[PDB]
Image (cartoon, coloured by chain):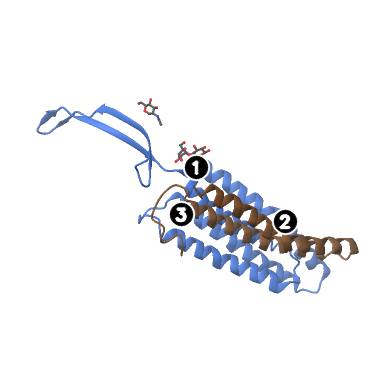
Amino acid sequence: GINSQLPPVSYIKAIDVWIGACMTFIFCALLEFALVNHIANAGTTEWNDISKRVDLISRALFPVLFFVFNILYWSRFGH
Amino acid sequence: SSSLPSFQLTNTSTTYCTSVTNTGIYSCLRTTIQLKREFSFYLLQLYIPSCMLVIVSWVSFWFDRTAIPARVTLGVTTLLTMTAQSAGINSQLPPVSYIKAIDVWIGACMTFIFCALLEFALVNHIANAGTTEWNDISKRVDLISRALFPVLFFVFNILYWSRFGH
Ligand SMILES: *[C@@H]1O[C@H](CO)[C@@H](O)[C@H](O)[C@H]1NC(C)=O
C-alpha cells in the first residue's frame, strides 16, 4: 500500500530503508520461533533449557535491537 | 546526471550519422546519452524481499511430519504472500508485453514456494503408511529438501545473474 503511492524513483528513499527494516524484523521474528521449535523437540533436559533461554533473550533482545536501529535511522535522516 | 528522475546518465557521445537516402546524401550529427538504472534501489525493493520469502518456505523442512498445522500454514501463507509480493511489483513495472528479467525472477520464486508447499504434500502422503520403511523414506525426503532447495536456488541464482549481468 505504501509502495504504490510513493512517486516513481529508482534510488533508495529513506522510507524504503525503513520498510525493508521492519520486513526484516518480522522475518527474524518468524525465524526465531523456528529455531526454538527445532531444539525443543529434543528430549534432553539441557536442550529444553536452551529453548527456553532463546525465548527469554528475544523477549528483550528484539526491542533493544529495533531501538538501536531506531536511533541509527532517525539520526541518519534527521538532517 | 542528478536531474534525471528514473535513470542515471553514465556517458555522452558526439558521432556522425550522415546517411544516404533515396533523395540523396545528407550530412547529419548525432549526440547520444547513455542511461542505466541504480541497481541498489531495485535490489532492496524487489529482490531482497522475495529472498526472505524463499528462505521462509525452507524452514518447513526442518519441522517434523507430525506437525500438520505448522507446515500447512507455513506453506500456504508463503505462497499467498508471494502472490501479493508479485502483485505489488507487477503493478509498477512499466507496461510491456515481453518477458522482463525481473519477471523471470518473480516466476522462479513463485515456483520454489510452489515446490516447497508441494514437498510437504509428498511427505504427508507416504508418512500415513504404517510401515517403518515408508517412514524412513518420509524422513529422508525432508532431510534432502533441507539442503536440496537452498542448493537448487543457489544454482538458479548463479544462472540468473550470469544471464542478466551483461
Ligand atoms: C563512454 O564513452 C567513451 C567515448 O566513446 C568510451 O571510450 C567508453 O568506453 C564509454 N564507457 C562505457 C560506459 O562504455
Q: Colour of chain A?
A: brown
Residue at coordinates 44% horizontally, 47% vertically from top-left? A11
Task: Check disc 3 and report its element: helix, strand or loop.
Answer: helix
Q: Residue beneath label 3, please?
A: B103
Label 3 sits on what residue type?
Answer: Asp
Across and down, in percent, residue B50 comes to 55, 56
* Host chain of mark 2: B
Q: Quadrant of the N terminus of chain B?
A: top left
> Which mark, residue A40?
none
Above or below for B161 versus B86:
above
Across and down, in percent, residue B48 comes to 55, 52
Q: Residue beneath label 1, please?
A: B163
Q: Residue beneath label 2, please?
A: B144
Above or below for B164 versus B118:
above
Across and down, in percent, residue A39 comes to 81, 61
Residue, far right: A45
